[PDB]
Amino acid sequence: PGRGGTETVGKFEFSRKDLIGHGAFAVVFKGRHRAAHDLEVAVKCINKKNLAKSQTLLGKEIKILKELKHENIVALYDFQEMANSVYLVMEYCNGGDLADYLHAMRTLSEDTIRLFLQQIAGAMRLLHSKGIIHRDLKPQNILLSNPAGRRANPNSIRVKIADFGFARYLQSNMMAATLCGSPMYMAPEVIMSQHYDGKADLWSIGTIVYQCLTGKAPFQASSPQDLRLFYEKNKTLVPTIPRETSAPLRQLLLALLQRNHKDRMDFDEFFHHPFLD
Ligand SMILES: NCCCNc1nc(Nc2cccc(NC(=O)N3CCCC3)c2)ncc1I
Picture 1 (cartoon, protein in one colour):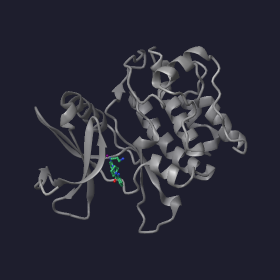
Picture 2 (cartoon, protein in one colour):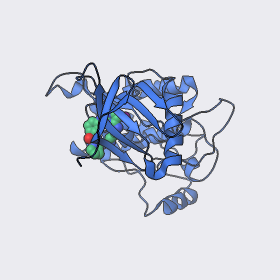
Picture 3 (cartoon, rainbow, N blue to C red):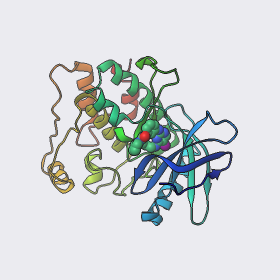
Picture 4 (cartoon, helix red, strand yellow):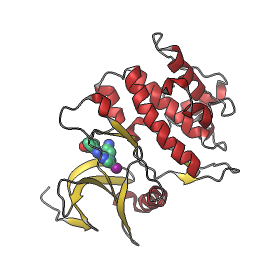
């Protein structure tokens, strides 16, 4: 309410006044550059209600993001890690998140989907070449930003992958096995407690595309336990795709949403899929 004075991290300032994100493991406040007030930032802070876990995730996010520079990955301007606190000063994305946008628009046209997926593909090319897997890709973690003025055209919307707290480096001859992510967007091999690799992110991207198209996640279950049982019991998974969907987009969706990671589209195939051209 009235409590809170100005906080500073390097050349940036913020207060608890303008909350723009809240989760179990992080809180995000709008801030600004101290010498240039028109330069907006998003400052991610520990959620002290889950202090240890929050501190871990923010620390991982710094380790990963300080090594990534790309338009389609949220920028890290600066950060401040200490024994009992952690702050990240990140790019302010002025369009909100993809989850709210796809819903407000009553789902997205194929042309808009292509525009956004081309950009997501560019960021994933960098993550793949750097040997990084994100592990929590979902519309809520794809942010929008439009560089043009007020009321600018939709064709100018740029997207940025955010929230890398669950990301890790994975050596190319190894597999990951940490059960983490968000159950409705998680690859079947992850939620079934198996080893997995970068192809898990490709499943999640498939689920993003599916939700942009329909407004819903592709496999509805009554609970995460029931969803795991569903994958475990059905070796053949096929989501309900609207009949008017173009054949090339339907093909891309079905290739990404393959239950078996061996059958699923690989990175090269994704980057070069004709829907993106
Ligand atoms: N879901 C928000 C993610 C938070 N993280 C970031 N968010 C933005 N930009 C940004 C712009 C407009 C609106 C919002 N969200 C909000 O205002 N609310 C959401 C809950 C309360 C109200 C967020 N930029 C960079 C980051 I990192």
